[PDB]
Length: 350
Image (cartoon, rainbow, N blue to C red; front, side):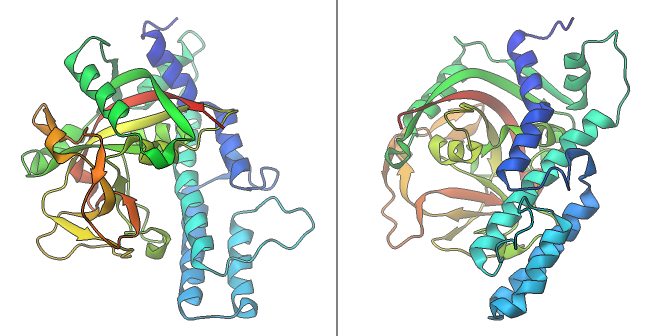
């Protein structure tokens, strides 16, 4: 039996759960009889992204529903959806492209998790929890509840839950300190950059095996840049509830995972509205989507030289913006250094 702390063992069990991967695919309307977990591949996912880009091109060029039908059908041929003997819904607009791009991002992480489970060795004498932990190539430790870092993290959670996200509240179950192998070395050129912030990144539990083993990634070249508000980058928030919404937890599945990453923001390119970019203008290191609300700048504190915007939400003074809250985007994977992973219990009031 494993000598790992019980919370670390529970975390490993959660992220490598095959039935959870299947459930996530069902939620996305994928036909598991036609496309089981074992049949997913990088090649097929990449081909589906490319077709989504074909659809995006027809969408921008104002193509008719009859003109788009073949392109829409090509997507379904590659990624079978649960529709029986019926005609599937038409992928004829920007919202459809965005939704399918999000689904493919998830499939890409699920394929990584499944490939780790299938591509190793079998030894019944070892605890499968230890075996699966080693596949993550990440040092995972439990943060002591009475420590300074635990106090700062709990305050960040307590203070940045938006009033507009009040259908639920959050309870921190466990706080883990994480160290992905080689990430500290990769981060070296950015470790002393100005404007380094400790920010939230929420994702479905089924993505975490992929995130821990490969780090946060940018959508592939084949992915449509218009499927993402600020293009193909890595997205973060300074409001815990804004990232917690991306966990996609429910009354029937109320436990979620959220990351705290040190993000080297540097010179921010400030935007109020969608800008589908792949590269930043010269001199810029990140995009800041300007929210109507921001954590109070006077309440910013420092945790190991990194700024933690844990103030309660106040008016930013930014007018006529598409964003209720701030968002931060980097376009180089080396600008992120993952620091903590929190296991959260979502208490739904609805």
